Amino acid sequence: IYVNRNMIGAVVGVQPFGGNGLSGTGPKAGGPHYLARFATEQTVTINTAAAG
Amino acid sequence: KLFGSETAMPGPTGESNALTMRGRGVFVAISPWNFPLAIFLGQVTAALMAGNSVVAKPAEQTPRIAREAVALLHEAGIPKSALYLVTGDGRIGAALTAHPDIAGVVFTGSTEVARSINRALAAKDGPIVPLIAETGGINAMIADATALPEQVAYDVVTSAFRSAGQRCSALRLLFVQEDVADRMIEMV
Amino acid sequence: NIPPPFTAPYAPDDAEIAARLLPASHLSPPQEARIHRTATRLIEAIRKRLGGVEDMLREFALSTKEGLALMVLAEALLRVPDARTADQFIEDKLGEGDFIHHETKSTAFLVNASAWARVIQPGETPDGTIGRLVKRLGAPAVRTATRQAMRLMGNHFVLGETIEQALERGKPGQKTRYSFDMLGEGARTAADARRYFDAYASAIETIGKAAGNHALPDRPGISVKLSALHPRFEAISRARVMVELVPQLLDLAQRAKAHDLNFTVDAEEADRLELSLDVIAATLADPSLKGWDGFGLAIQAYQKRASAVIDYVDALARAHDRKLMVRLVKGAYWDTEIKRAQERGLDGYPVFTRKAMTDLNYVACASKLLALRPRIFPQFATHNALTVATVLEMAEGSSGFEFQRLHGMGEALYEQLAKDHADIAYRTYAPVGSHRDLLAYLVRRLLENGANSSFVAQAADYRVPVPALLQRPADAIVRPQAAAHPRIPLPCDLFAPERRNSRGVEFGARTALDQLLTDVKAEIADATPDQAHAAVAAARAGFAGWSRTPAGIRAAALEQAAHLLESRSAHFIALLQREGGKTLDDALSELREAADFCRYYAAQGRKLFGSETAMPGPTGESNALTMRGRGVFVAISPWNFPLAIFLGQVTAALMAGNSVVAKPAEQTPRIAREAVALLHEAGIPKSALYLVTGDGRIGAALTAHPDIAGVVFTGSTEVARSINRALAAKDGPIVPLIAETGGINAMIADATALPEQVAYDVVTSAFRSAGQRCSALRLLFVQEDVADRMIEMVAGAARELKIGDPSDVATHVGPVIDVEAKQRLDAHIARMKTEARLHFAGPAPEGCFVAPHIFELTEAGQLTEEVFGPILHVVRYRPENLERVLRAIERTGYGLTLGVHSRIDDSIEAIIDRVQVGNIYVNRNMIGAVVGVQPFGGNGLSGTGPKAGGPHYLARFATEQTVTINTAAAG
Amino acid sequence: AYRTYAPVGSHRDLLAYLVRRLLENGANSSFVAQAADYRVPVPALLQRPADAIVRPQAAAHPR
Ligand SMILES: Cc1cc2nc3c(=O)[nH]c(=O)nc-3n(C[C@H](O)[C@H](O)[C@H](O)COP(=O)(O)OP(=O)(O)OC[C@H]3O[C@@H](n4cnc5c(N)ncnc54)[C@H](O)[C@@H]3O)c2cc1C
Ligand SMILES: Cc1cc2nc3c(=O)[nH]c(=O)nc-3n(C[C@H](O)[C@H](O)[C@H](O)COP(=O)(O)OP(=O)(O)OC[C@H]3O[C@@H](n4cnc5c(N)ncnc54)[C@H](O)[C@@H]3O)c2cc1C
């Protein structure tokens, strides 16, 4: 949403760009939720008691 | 920030728990003609950064800028084995996305093509992979009678006609209050 | 009158205890002056300075793991028939290479003597515990440390391949100079419990033939552990324990009595205290033990119940008119007790959390025991010079008690005491047993010697001034309110201040278990396709308002749901047992997890949706990023966690600002309905949450509905694909699909792994909840050198599982969900019987039950399907072929959980680097993922992500919005 | 080839010599002191001096 200015030229890291509905899936390019979608999470759980 | 170090999780004594994020596999990156360098590079560098190798098919109208961007990434330190450029039509794009070994698709282009990519992915008996699709818009602007007509006109002309309107963000539909309608339209 | 079954409050307040112990600890200045002098002299003797384990750890700056590795290597090297062969190995081979091979072979030697009996290429990358040690210290120092470990293993331990070999080795017409601390503990199989019984019986005869001609207490003793004598020694199996174990313990007591020996029942974990006292009381009660003063037990001063145990033992002694020998110790399982109370969400710790509190309680308990002479003969087991000096002073004169130490500890301490006070008696114990029981004993011992708080460790460190060792415990505590350790939170505060932790129950406390069993015992038409469509439309109408309800109010609603869940835990636990067929621990755990989901998503919800994120940019412009609800989410949940996964998915979607239409598994709609009613009562509007029950056709109507904004799904891989296809066929928006599906989960156990622990964790991972967990172990890979022992131990342990009615507290394995499931399982069993070796097939009760089964495959590729039941598959492998194991795990295409059991960090790390599995568990079981601790969920055929119970979950239920305002006209 | 020296002299000259010698053996920076301390990993003793300084402006001791 752009208020009292034009609607174009989204700046990377300033206006994370991208929409919903028929406009896209997300996440927004140039924003902080983008990179995670390209990755998978991994939890490593180690029982450390024999060491202290 | 995201992949540079693990996130420690709180838990009981005598046990460690760490959350990490790793690459998924092979990403297919499909880019449009209207931002042939920046969207091409945005999608590709994101996938690479996340630890994925990338097969990139640029829009048929703009392969040369894509080839140069690819060579530039290789020279910037991206291994030849991590990044490949495949040029061609939509059937080639369909070949890459229907390939059973890829780990995800990042797509920017038409809504119709995104749906067919999504259908080709879902048809596979393999893993359900991520689809990142940024498609079009029918973008509105609402201008009320408190708005400055000289500024509305300028921002409307810019939003609609910059780049011959060949931007996904471009203004397509202007709503203007009737009391100021004649003046604003005439000025645009 | 015989005392009632022991029941003391499990974890009372530390401060109230300190308020009584602090003043009673007061001693007159001449009393303190005498203690100070005796202790100074004992400590100075210790600092005179071959020594002990603490010295080896200190001298080479060894971790506990490294000490363990060298002692194991040392023991193998000592049992080579020709000592010159050992010398050649140490100089030529050790430190030059084959580091992992040496670590693996010497550890395997302990269960498989034949395994241990190449040419080492130069420039080998130093990996493994020994390799890393060599890199840090250098090969020659490692050789020097190994020889020292050889002296320690040879001098301070009585060991053999069998008990007869150990007993022969430790032989003195002389009397034995030491009593026997028998190695065994925690039998996993019936065969193990008999072997330990036999070893105890053999030891009693060996020690009896060399017991000398004096009267008690001047005769040797033997220490015995109840967990070694019974393979399911636990409160829930009490009925069978009283019936099977008591006669065994009695048999041994009688054999000890016939040689007039000291016979001591060791004290183990806090959750076994009450059960051990029941066993000991019933055993002591037997008339055959009259006329003998050598029977006794250990009492741990680190426990708040310690004083009450002393009263109980004394009343037991008077009721039966016996004399007892009672060992007072501090306690060997402190770290274990902390960990457990935390995992189990107990309301406090059974032990003190400041070391000085244990020291105080020890002296108070000793004072109490001294006053119970001569009926009770106290034995003060400690290597603390100050504790010895203080107990000696309190005795004011002496006799009617003794001190106790472990061979290889407190030698100089007790020699000096005997010089300075000739009528002081002290008993010395030597560890005696088989190599197969060494590892478990060594680990515990190395934790005490390596501990920074250890008195023995400090007295040997010349950086620690003698006067620091003499600080009186009361002066360390100073004030009652400081009794609890400031840096150790109560389990309820484990996640503070981020969120509250759910409450658990300690089954080892009979008051708590009986109350829980009592409370629990005291406690649906389908939908038409039209009804499901109306539910969607209704949820669609409720979306606008709910999405705009402030995040803190949505969060308050989840938190109230958690509170109502815990307040009504008995009600929901009853439902989990009746509808889900879950055993009590599984039901309780599911209830905790459900509450945990509500609190964690609430807390992550405020963080993520509580306020906008400001984005940096030019002046004269603001840029704010927000996350809003998507629309109507369809939540489809499975039968195996019918409350927690159902609630996790639903409360997540709700928290993100979505309205929800929820379709629960056909087998478990009732718990779902109650959960829904509960969320509504917690503050979730009727218009935001709807329950639609029915089959997959109803589930399919919901997912094909053109107006929904997303699907969250947990279930079968095939159903997830058909949902994905139904969504992708739509001409509408591409909506998010979150799908957590199955796994074919592997465990890799190498020859450095402890078989008793592997067996326990394998049996748990594969057979808990009748294998009806998505994280369950299906495929065990075990190195060939330890395969026979490991498989045998797993099979023997599986046989001890009680299969039956999940409402009986003694049951370990309940029924499978329905006949359709049982049938599918039985077909796979019939197939595997014709296809693979059957190692174990248990006896199912009549009804919808499948018993644990263990099959060995020739290759992993013979297991091609997730089999959703208590059915373990085993593949043995050669150490050089680890890649083929890893390749076989990749081949399935699944990636949910993976277990790794190994001592070797480089091996563990290589496995982690290689595999893509969502949850890797190292040296523990693979189940019971805790919300916010183990973000759970996999990749490949196992799921889409993001992980449930983790920090990337909520975002996916939302969509982002950037608002960009040109602010220049304001300034 | 390596030459080995032994300290030779009268008791009346020992104290002054001993003080200086004990300052070198007791110094935390001493290589001999570190190589004898098993807490110090062999690789730490092998850090190249140029890698400790890294940059000219860091030549002087900051403290
Ligand atoms: C012959 C013999 C038999 C034994 N049998 C048993 C047995 O059957 N069962 C058993 O549990 N123990 C038993 N022990 C005791 C155990 O093995 C340790 O030796 C003992 O706890 C050490 O106490 P201490 O006076 O030697 O040493 P210290 O260094 O004085 O005391 C150490 C002890 O303090 C306690 N401690 C450490 N940190 C904390 C803390 N933060 N808060 C509260 N307390 C803390 C622990 O119990 C620890 O062991 C036995 C010991 C001997 C010598
Ligand atoms: C046979 C023999 C004869 C010697 N004769 C003399 C002599 O005639 N005159 C003399 O001055 N020395 C003399 N020395 C050297 C002195 O006695 C020390 O032995 C020597 O400096 C140690 O250096 P290193 O390579 O052994 O040890 P290292 O542990 O490598 O180096 C220690 C040296 O580093 C230097 N150093 C320590 N801290 C700092 C710092 N913050 N900044 C800069 N430098 C620092 C000091 O010089 C210190 O001695 C002699 C040594 C030997 C073996």
Image (cartoon, rainbow, N blue to C red):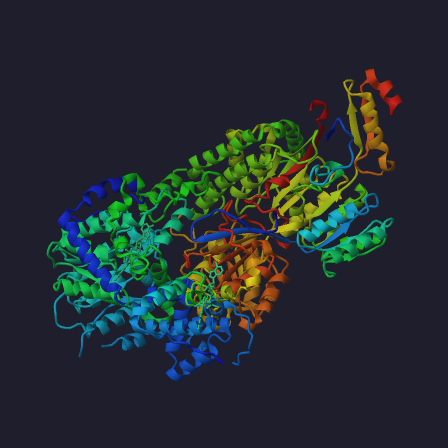
Q: Residue at x 69, y 31 (%)?
A: C619
Please identify the quarter of the rendering in which residue C392 is found: bottom left
Q: Residue at x 79, y 21 (%)?
A: B148
Front-lying residue, C602 or C467: C467
Single out the residue that lies furthest toward the left. C397
Measured as percent of width and height from the top left, residue C116 is found at 44, 77
Q: Is residue C358 left or right of residue C117?
A: left
Front-lying residue, D40 or B51: D40
Single out the residue that lies furthest toward the top. B179
Q: Is residue D60 left or right of residue C632?
A: left
Measured as percent of width and height from the top left, residue C120 is found at 53, 79
**Vertical comparison of B165 with C120: above or below:** above
Q: Is residue C777 left or right of residue C916?
A: left
Front-lying residue, C286 or C347: C347
Q: Tag count in the figure?
A: 0
| Residue C781 in sight in this render | yes
Measured as percent of width and height from the top left, residue C792 is found at 44, 68
Single out the residue that lies furthest toward the right. B186
Measured as percent of width and height from the top left, residue C917 is found at 59, 56
| Residue C284 in sight in this render | no
User: Ligand 1, what quadrant?
Assistant: bottom left
